[PDB]
């Protein structure tokens, strides 16, 4: 009969997937492309290439891979932080919903992975590009897992500066290392230590500017993040016996508040009571002087 | 002095990660392991192996891969359907939160991928295994993305039965094909892929059917507004017969995202008395199983397998 014949045809062919289908599920992703991201990224990749010297067409693919992983990971990051804005517009998950956004972001992680084989035909080198991809993706999720856990289960764990830096080495260092390691493996004195330093500077600076200044006003406070200035402050208050301030910092973080005055109060506690903002600014300058007093690093 | 020296050490070493850090991010995953569920998956693998003959240690790994992807995919599946229960207990995202559960599930996807790399060191075969893994994960997400889309954009698109089957081929068939293709690529010793595709289709339709049938005998699929196989039949049946009020009433209840049992029973009544969608589905599953039962030639089958098939019969 015809039903059996049609079922037979179905199971003997590859799953049917159309262009229209590809478009429908790409919506959460297409939305974040509507706004440009730091364009100075292909900029960073172009700099590092002065040293790696990859051929233009191979470099392009590395760039596409990292751009894709980066843009899609932001979709997930914003769900995980329940963020309202990204690149000055509403986050995808508030528009298309959390379910679609998770699935689309995860879909793009595997599309990124598929691009890797466009880099080489040589089994050995391929094997190493894949291992690098797998390793850093593992590191990336270990660090983000720690960051989310500390924030969502606060005050169960109050991280020390040491713990925060290790989380960053996993998370933000993971994407910087991913980009550098792929290029070093493709290139015809590794820069890994230098790229780890850059990732840390970047994350701490990112935490700092969030309070010093589109994602909204000091949105890291609304999200309750254990940011670099917050970690210094929680440890500073514990160490100095400032019991009341230590507890009020925790309380404000736990409110997940959008109240601008409450956020401003916390920011001035970091300014005048714990001097965490100045501590952070100096810490950043000290890391930068590690490069300078030893060009990309200029941002 | 000191700070700089601590930073030098940090950036020159691999990222620090401990056993304690591993236990913390594994919490959402271990929770679902608290109940084994219908873990007889290891059985289908173990059985298919009688034809594939993979050495016991490679078989263990394929096994771990399948268990990891399947377990972590339910963590994500439950967040995507906002499900309250899984394997009889509160879903992980409701205990550990949506953020940690997504991250933990995604972490396990990559730990599964790293196991793939440990199946062989033959560089060519390795590339093939990675290609299979990559291809099926992509089909899986396309299928799940389409199922979610219809559900969340309802009533913009009402899929037909043919559309539903293509979605299922991508989604459900993705993990069955993934296990089978890996096993087949590894075998020392006609693909069983067509057979496994059919199994995945039977499995999913049967799953849609029992979700409504066990309630007739939670029916969370109704609360989620899912375009399940019986609901798809019911929507196209009412459209075809020009039954406007019934068509609309089915949409209204799905759109309600209701957990009110009397309303859920009302949709089931519609399916039972107006469209006869449950009898239709039962019969459709029977016709699929019979394609295996009457495969005298063994066009699809290589007995322990047929038993499974007949079991799935409704
Ligand atoms: O892309 P966006 O400008 O939205 C932003 O994520 C900037 C950013 C934050 C963190 C990491 C990166 C980053 C780091 C390393 C490499 C690359 C990054 O972004 C891209 C894009 C394209 C290629 C490589 C990278 C960019 P944002 O915090 O300013 O929103
Ligand atoms: O570190 P922040 O989250 O503060 C930020 O830099 C963005 C960011 C930087 C580096 C990594 C990630 C991130 C977060 C969640 C998941 C993943 C991330 O990066 C990858 C890459 C590939 C897969 C998953 C993830 C986000 P921001 O642009 O939101 O300021
Ligand atoms: O794991 P649970 O027992 O929780 C459940 O997913 C049922 C189930 C149990 C075991 C395996 C599977 C399953 C699902 C999709 C694909 C495959 C499954 O098992 C195998 C084995 C070999 C290949 C593919 C699959 C489903 P449930 O729907 O009853 O919650
Ligand atoms: O298809 P249903 O959601 O009805 C169910 O069969 C479970 C299921 C089967 C097959 C695939 C999936 C699924 C859903 C979302 C994401 C992913 C799924 O399977 C994988 C494997 C690997 C990565 C992601 C996913 C879920 P159930 O046990 O919840 O009834």
Image (cartoon, coloured by chain):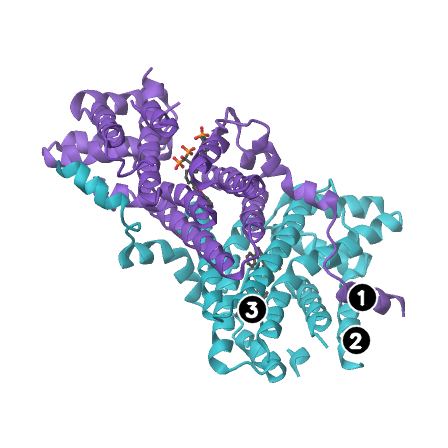
Chain colours: A cyan, B purple
Q: Which of the labelled discs sits on residue B7, or is there none?
A: 1
Helix, strand or loop at label 3? It is helix
Q: Quadrant of residue A230?
A: bottom right
How far apart, in angstroms, are the residues tagged by discs 3 and 2? 33 Å
Residue position marked by numbered label 2 in the rendering: A290
How far apart, in angstroms, are the residues tagged by discs 3 and 1? 32 Å
| Residue B275 appearing in the image | yes
Of B144 and A187, which appears nearest the observer? A187
Residue A7, given in percent of the width and then of the height, sits at 22, 40
Task: Single out the mark in the foreground, 3 or 1.
Answer: 3
Residue position marked by numbered label 3 in the rendering: A125
The picture quadrant for ligand 1 comes to bottom right
Helix, strand or loop at label 1? It is helix
Q: Residue at x 78, y 51 (%)?
A: A234
Of A196 and A299, which appears nearest the observer? A196
Q: In the figure, A102 relative to A170: above or below?
A: above
Residue count near mark 1 (Cα–Cα under 10 Å), binned few <14, some 14–19, many ≥20: some
Name the outermost residue toward the top. B217
Q: Quadrant of residue A227?
A: bottom right
Answer with mark 3 or mark 2, whichever residue precedes in sequence.
3
Q: Callout 1: residue from which chain?
A: B
Residue B224, given in percent of the width and then of the height, sits at 37, 34
Q: Residue at x 77, y 67 (%)?
A: B12
Task: Single out the mark in the foreground, 3 or 2.
Answer: 3
């Amino acid at each position: 009969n015809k039903m059996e014949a049609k079922i037979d045809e179905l199971i003997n062919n590859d799953p049917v997937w159309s262009s229209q289908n590809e478009s429908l599920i790409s919506k959460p992703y297409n939305h974040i492309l509507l706004k440009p991201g730091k364009n100075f990224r292909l900029n960073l990749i172009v700099q590092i290439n002065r040293v790696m010297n990859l051929p233009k067409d191979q470099l392009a693919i590395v760039s596409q891979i990292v751009e894709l992983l980066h843009n899609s990971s932001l979709l997930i990051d914003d769900i995980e932080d329940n963020a309202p804005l990204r690149r000055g517009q509403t986050t995808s998950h508030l528009i298309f919903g959390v379910p679609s956004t998770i699935n689309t972001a995860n879909y793009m992680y595997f599309r990124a992975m598929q691009l890797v084989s466009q880099l080489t035909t040589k089994e050995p080198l391929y094997h190493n590009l894949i291992t690098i991809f797998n390793e850093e993706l593992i590191n990336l999720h270990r660090g983000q897992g720690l960051d989310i856990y500390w924030r969502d289960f606060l005050p169960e764990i109050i991280p020390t500066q040491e713990m925060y830096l290790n989380m960053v080495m996993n998370k933000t260092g993971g994407l910087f290392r991913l980009t550098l390691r792929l290029m070093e493996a493709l290139s015809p004195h590794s820069l890994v230590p230098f790229i780890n330093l850059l990732g840390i500077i970047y994350q701490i600076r990112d935490d700092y500017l969030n309070l010093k200044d589109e994602k909204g006003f000091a949105e890291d406070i609304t999200e309750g993040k254990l940011s670099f200035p917050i970690v210094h402050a929680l440890n500073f208050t514990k160490t100095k016996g400032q019991t009341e301030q230590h507890n009020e910092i925790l309380r404000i973080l736990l409110l997940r508040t959008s109240d601008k005055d409450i956020k401003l109060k916390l920011i001035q506690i970091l300014e005048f009571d714990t001097n965490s903002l100045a501590y952070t600014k100096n810490f950043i300058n000290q890391l930068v002087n590690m490069i300078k007093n030893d060009y990309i690093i200029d941002h």
